[PDB]
Amino acid sequence: RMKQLEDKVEELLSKAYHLENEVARLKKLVGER
Amino acid sequence: RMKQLEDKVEELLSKAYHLENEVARLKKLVGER
Amino acid sequence: RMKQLEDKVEELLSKAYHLENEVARLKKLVGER
């Protein structure tokens, strides 16, 4: 039960990370914050 | 207890899934650099 | 284990929240819904 959850979380951790970078970038190809 | 976390990880999975979709769509729509 | 996981889940909750917000604004700024 433990591993699965942690497995799960590092994966989620990976996605959100990539996501922030993508948004950051989309934030420039428009009007810089 | 873990059914909890396995629940709070379940909302995150769903959150990340929609967020990924939204970001892909915009990425497409925006377009430029 | 648990303080770590539970703390990792908060990191995640934090970021999903930020991201959602950023994405939401990004969609008003470009007219997309």
Image (cartoon, coloured by chain):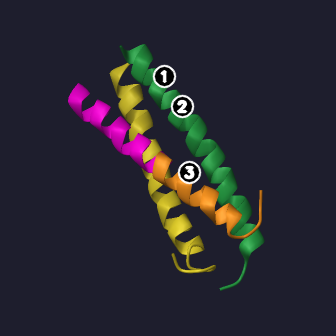
Chain colours: A yellow, B green, C orange
Q: Quadrant of residue C22?
A: bottom right
The disc placed on residue C20 is: 3
Front residue of this view, candidates B13 and A6: B13
Query: Marks 1 and 3: which is nearer the front?
Result: 3
Give the amino acid type for the residue marked by disc 1 in the picture: Asp
Residue drawn at point x = 30 percent, y = 32 percent: C5
Residue drawn at point x = 28 percent, y = 36 percent: C7
- Give the magenta-colored segment's residue range: C1-16
The disc placed on residue B11 is: 2
The image position of residue C32, as x and y in percent, is 77, 62
Query: Is residue C30 found left or right of A26 in the rendered image?
Result: right
As helix, strand or loop, the secondary structure at mark 1 comes to helix
Count of all numbered marks drawn on residues in the image: 3
Residue drawn at point x = 62 percent, y = 52 percent: B20
Query: Marks 3 and 2: which is nearer the front?
Result: 3
Q: Quadrant of residue C8?
A: top left
As helix, strand or loop, the secondary structure at mark 2 comes to helix
Q: Mark 3–mark 2 contact, CB under 8 Å?
A: no
Image vertical order of residue B4 relative to residue C14, above or below: above
The image position of residue A31, as x and y in percent, is 59, 80
Instruction: Identify residue for label 1.
Output: B7
The image position of residue A5, as x and y in percent, is 40, 28
Q: Is residue C22 visible?
A: yes
Image vertical order of residue C5 relative to residue A23, above or below: above
Give the amino acid type for the residue marked by disc 3 in the picture: Glu
